[PDB]
Image (spheres, coloured by chain):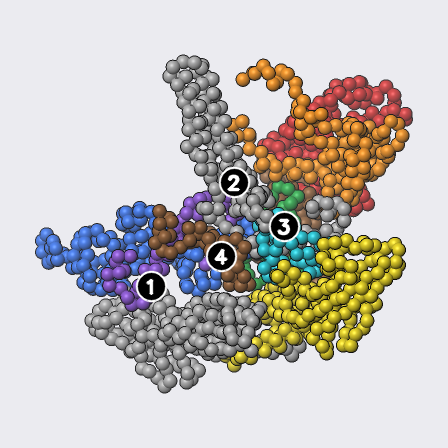
Chain colours: A green, B purple, C yellow, E blue, F cyan, G brown, H orange, J red
Amino acid sequence: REEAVVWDILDEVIREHPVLLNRAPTLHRLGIQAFEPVLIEGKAIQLHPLV
Amino acid sequence: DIVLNPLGVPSRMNIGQILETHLGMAAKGIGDKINAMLKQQQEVAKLREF
Amino acid sequence: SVTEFLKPRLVDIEQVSSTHAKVTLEPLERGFGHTLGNALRRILLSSMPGCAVTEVEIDGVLHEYSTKEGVQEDILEILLNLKGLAVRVQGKDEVILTLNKSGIGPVTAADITHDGDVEIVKPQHVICHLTDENASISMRIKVQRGRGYVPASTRIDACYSPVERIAYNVEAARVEQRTDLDKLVIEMETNGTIDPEEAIRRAATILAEQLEAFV
Amino acid sequence: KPRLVDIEQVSSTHAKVTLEPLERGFGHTLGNALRRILLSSMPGCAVTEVEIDGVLHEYSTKEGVQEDILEILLNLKGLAVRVQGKDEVILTLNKSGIGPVTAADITHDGDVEIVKPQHVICHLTDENASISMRIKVQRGRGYVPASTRIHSEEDERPIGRLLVDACYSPVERIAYNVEAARVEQRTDLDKLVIEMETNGTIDPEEAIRRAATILAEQLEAFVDL
Amino acid sequence: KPLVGTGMERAVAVDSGVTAVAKRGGVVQYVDASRIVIKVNEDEMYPGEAGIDIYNLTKYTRSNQNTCINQMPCVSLGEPVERGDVLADGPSTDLGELALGQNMRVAFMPWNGYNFEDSILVSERVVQEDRFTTIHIQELACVSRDTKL
Amino acid sequence: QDVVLGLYYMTRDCVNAKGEGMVLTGPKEAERLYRSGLASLHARVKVRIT
Amino acid sequence: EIKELLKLGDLPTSGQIRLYDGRTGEQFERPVTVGYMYMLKLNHLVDDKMHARSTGSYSLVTQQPLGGKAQFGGQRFGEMEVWALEAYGAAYTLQEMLTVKSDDVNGRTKMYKNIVDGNHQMEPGMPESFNVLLKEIRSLGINIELED
Amino acid sequence: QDLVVTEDDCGTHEGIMMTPVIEGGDVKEPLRDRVLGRVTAEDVLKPGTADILVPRNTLLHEQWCDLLEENSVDAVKVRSVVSCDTDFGVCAHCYGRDLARGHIINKGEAIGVIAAQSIGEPGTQLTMRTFHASRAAAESSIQVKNK
Amino acid sequence: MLNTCYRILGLKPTVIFADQIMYTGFAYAARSGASVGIDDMVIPEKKHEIISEAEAEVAEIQEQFQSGLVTAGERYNKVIDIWAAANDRVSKAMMDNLQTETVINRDGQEEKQVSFNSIYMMADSGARGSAAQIRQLAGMRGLMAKPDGSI
Amino acid sequence: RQMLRKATIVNAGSSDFLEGEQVEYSRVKIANRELEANGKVGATYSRDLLGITKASLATESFISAASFQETTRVLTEAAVAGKRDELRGLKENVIVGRLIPAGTGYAYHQDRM
């Protein structure tokens, strides 16, 4: 049914467990670069501009 | 309403983008004027001549 | 009610020394991190009453662009050393003071005649240095009262602000049954004779003073 | 202190307010601060829940009308309401015949008063047509779709009440100007001349007074701490 | 619509067959949302019983690529019509002009890089004006039977 | 794109600007040029850089 | 033609007006060009490309998940990302994708036992999909049996 | 595929000399970019003293030492992946040290994959080269621009 | 610079340097608030000169076609080389009538500066791409060969 | 530095006269012969140096060869030649669910093998 309390509990793990992200084509050692997750309330995934 | 980047415009190439936009303003700038004649309840002969 | 909302709550301040400060704010609505944040930037710069150096008469020099006999620091350098010097005045409005100094040693800051209603906050300030032989300077300094900055170019430089630097940051935050809320993290630096709490409280009451008529 | 005097009132909808006295960093501040107050945080009135007599679900076509329901939903969104007397009221649109649907022709219940009469909500084509809309209104603060109402439910038994994207803000447009000024016995002042447009849902004085007290409300904590 | 047009728009929508194309010329009888009926007056039919043109307007219908197709009226309640005039605009069409998308206020500067890499900001007055609203329509089908008992 | 540019867009031998040349210590700098009149670009201002 | 129409409607020839920000309030140093682009919308929206599925169903050939846009949220890795993965100096983040949690259903299910509590440590055995290497060659008419 | 760092170090002290290409006219390639992170075997600069050491590092600091001072010395001895004792895998002192955080990362590391992937993406950069007189004056006669 | 950050300093301090280059460097991009306009860029007024020179220099050889002074194979090459001589000239005439054109009075009056307009501060800075790209929008169109390879 | 490996054998001994052998066989065989085992059999190796296709064909692995190359031939080849894997490289380990020496792996593979 989806709940409000669930969100609050899962704010804790996000800092403790990272995310590994890549493109559809990857060739370098610059593909599988991984990032620490941070809380956001928006569908489309925000990131750095350098990487 | 929308905001674009000016950074793609010189890398790959569009001048039509520039022209359409400045003409879009030009089209709607004349458009903004013509409403006022009707927004003030003026009308009669003048609207035609503009 | 159906018109009321929830007001902000500070109580998360990173207090590092008397001079610098790093305040945070957990709750603020959409539209309200950017407002107040930017409004107070343009309050805490122009409208900040302090005390600073204005007009000065040199004993052996008339015009600024000269070089003194037996000193390393130029006048243009020393002008700026005087600008950053911090003063509090309670009783009077405007006072004329003197810098009687001579000998082998560094120019401190205390060696002024502590006049009537004059209180200085900082003693270790390097205004100048004196070199070989004895040397001697006796500056007839004058001070005025103001509100904002007035430079020398406009005067056909005074520094009337306790605020050194202003930087407000805006970042996202999470709360229970909500979408997005703008956290106001405010980075401030003061040195014009004012602790961070009093400045903001004054700026808030001065805003309140202006907004009293509006209400 | 400043002085709220000298307002150029042109009609009930549009407004051009002026402010003679304000200090040197205070024309620009409050001017821009209130821009971002008078848009999101604006208590007004708009359409929420509506029961059709002859239709239960949207996505259909009425017998003897040009305009579709999805079109008409949006016609209702842009409609302007003023309420003084109660909190929430249920009203009816009893209309029939060959003629264009105006805006007034409702039973003016207790303390209900409309500001704008010439609004085209619909058109009727056929001779002996008839519609009798059981419209409902709520009270709010910001713009509201419907999803947040679904999240908080409990005792729920309506289906026929078709939902319309709500538009709780009176303000159409915001523009503050800043110019320099001369006044007897003073040095320099930034005059705040404020150009405002409202949907017919709030008069200029109340909006600003609310925004000032709402600012005061937020600044109460700042002054206290 | 497009307010910067070209000139081609008037021939394309008519020869498409999407929008309701008037074959003959007369005067509109009864405009409804559902169907538009039109008296001929000018010619009259060959065997008898006058002209009378009728148009069954297609609404809330489906396509192959999961979308909505709605035909909508244009000309007023009882107005005259000529041979080859648009009566009802289809989906994403308006007064003999091909609309497709919409008219947008667009600026050409960065905004602390919320436009970094050819990305777009958008204001809330876009979404609030109820502009780009679309129905993505899907077939959810079932077969039960086919037995020998 | 937007990173690179911004930095030069600030760090430039600018044509005149409002200022000519008013000398500043260090902490006072950024602000005077952010505050009023004095732009951000200028060209030519000397500083007690630590 | 542009400018004469711009002249008919009281507009700048530059097409550049220095505008006061709705945010901060201040004007820009240079004059920002503003226009109307006539932006349009396109088909492949969020939902078409966006997929994410944890655990559930599997394909019929091998004990692997399914193709895509039908049953399980697979989303393939390919040869390109493996060559990538190996170089990233990581033994686990390869094995987890190709032994622990893909090719083995039961390898997931004995690890469903190990993850939740927080006990950890790995045991694979044989990687299931490669028995199809062995078997298809066995049926080819060649002999393969795990001897020694 | 399988060609990687194992073990400690190269025992043998032989290698390929490092020069610039010195192509035709002006300096197309300098000495500075070449030596970056490449170990010294013996390497004698000056007219017979010491300068460079038997195993020590050519990171970032000793470069400006050998490139601002003693500019006359153009040719210097340098090691290579082939030039090692142990043959299974390859020895660490031979290669070079091109990396991210700290210079020289740990023992037992991929290498062969670094290059092949770092030549992988510039395999998109090259474009097959897109459609790219005999005067008896300027070419037959050799000309010098600088003093 | 970040090179010399990371080469001199280390790991602990150099993160602080690079961060701002983004966050502030973007904040620096908006505050300027430049433009993409028609008048932002200025083509040289002498068009009918270097082009007609390129025309006439070729027409001089094109008369040598019709009459007979050059050889048929080299005739293409000489016409091309003479056209292509002016292509670089128009591009250089562009680059000079663009970059080093300010003319402004600084207190004591009459002074030349580096012109900081729209696309210069895209290019000089180094956003992306190059100068040969910009020239197209501006002056001369890039020459594309026949399907075989020759021009 | 990876290509330069295969070699035609020069001298006669335990090696096969003038056949095909790698650098890893050649150098180790030469080295062990010097001052313990046998002087003369100490055979030199003249170089056989190839391109991307032909050199990579020579895999000591019979799991791996039987994937990259035309598996029409090589799975049948590893079968026909009765070849037994017993390798400790990165090829075979990705496949049959064994551990690659890679990064931290090396620390374990130094203790294990």
Q: Residues within 10 Å of mark 3 (few under 14, many from 20)?
A: some
Q: Is label 3 in contact with label 2 (beta carbons under 8 Å)? A: no
The residue wearing badge 4 is: G18
Q: Say what secondary structure mark 1 lies in.
A: helix
Q: Is residue C113 above or below residue J37?
A: below
Q: Residues within 10 Å of mark 2 (few under 14, many from 20)?
A: some
Q: Three-letter amino acid code at disc 3? A: Ala
Q: Chain of mark 4?
A: G
Front one among H106 and C55: C55
Q: Chain of mark 3?
A: F
Q: Three-letter amino acid code at disc 1? A: Ala
| Relative horizontal placement of residue E61, taking residue H49 as reference (left or right) | left
Q: Residue at x 57, y 47 (%)?
A: I109
The residue wearing badge 1 is: B36
Front one among A32 and C72: C72
CA gap, disc 3 to disc 1?
Answer: 47 Å
Identify the mark at residue F43; answer none if there is no mark.
Answer: 3
Find residue J53 and report its horizontal and vertical position in percent: 63, 29
| Relative horizontal placement of residue A15, taking residue I99 as reference (left or right) | right
Q: Three-letter amino acid code at disc 4? A: Arg
Find residue A37 and report its horizontal and vertical position in percent: 64, 58
Q: Three-letter amino acid code at disc 2? A: Leu
The image quarter in which residue H124 lies:
top right
The residue wearing badge 2 is: I98
Q: Chain of mark 1?
A: B
